[PDB]
Length: 509
Image 1 (cartoon, rainbow, N blue to C red):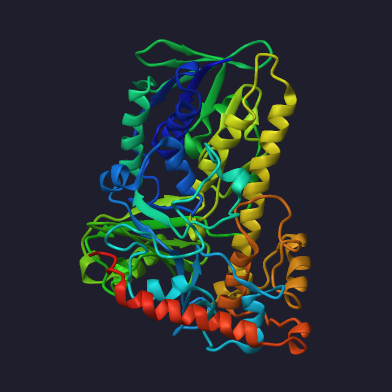
Image 2 (cartoon, one colour):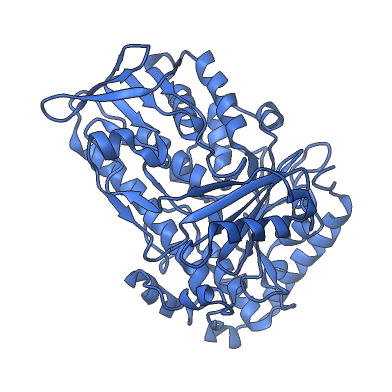
């Protein structure tokens, strides 16, 4: 097998084409058929620290692609007013240090220098606080455990690294601009680009896809079909009738209103991070881009009207958002039961979707195409490839959903009906059991969702410590161990961070 038809463009379709091409070159034949515009959600989009492997896999260095997509640096997610109104904190991309067997955050709970766990435990938090770049002007990355000039595995993909060493950042960028960039990347390497629509998905007597019918380009045939039609699920959900599994009962945010301005009123747009500011019925995002800032209100319609959400958004961004276009959309929250069915693989919103609270969307796609390459079938179509693939991506989505639920379960604020309901909504049975563990021992490699889903224990720690709604305790053993080494670890971090504050350039500059 080496004939691939990708239905759908945008970020999902073209990450698929460009990644297949980077992996297989002239030995894979790819045709992508696309129509266009859906709105995505907002203009801007954000990624995990994983995304680094994607671009390196393609042989793309930052200078080649970042200017073309108006890309900025993302060093964390900045969560505002989830605990209380004065309050914010970071979920950064920085490894969690440990001392004599315990995570620094455990020490922090016992003998932490300040009341800010993230500033105490993370070099990145100060860097971001000062609106600083993670790179020196000559180009040298911030002295961190990650040696960028160090030996790595050739063709290193995210799903065997799994954050074992920590690259210090991710990106924010204009999603349509990345699709256009990858379009070029892909077409240069021999991907055939067809702008048209699909009128019909042709099935054979076993219900397998034989080809798709276009308006003006005839029938597009091939061995393997990639469904990148988004919420439509034109191939996987419609032609092949694969059922959808909703996450709505645990994550009720079902709606979004979005817009863009050249600059944010509180200047969240200067910060080298993505901001999630909690609201009365959800939360507003801020995504910094080079010459613009994208903003949106993710909310639950049962609590808030579309008109209300838009007015809140406009006021929140300020006088610059008085008159600009606002785009509303509704979200399909959950995943397909199986993202690979017969000879069809869904990648992107067709495979599944969660609110972009931790901006996992591109991550879901990156993981999917990697798994596609990994479990790529031969012409015997051994069903095990499919089972392995589906196991891998369902775990990723289910794991992240659990992680997102925690954001609301742990959030301390309780001042609207919506925020009260976050403590009474159904949760995964597994999650409640894990929360009981975390009350006594901070999130551990053994007490998180046990399959790969992109999030190390320290991510869970950050949410717990930051949202402050779950009472937490340090390990009893810390009362018996010498605290000296930990204090010297806090001190090393503080010194590094006050040195760094002086010599790093600002984000926009």
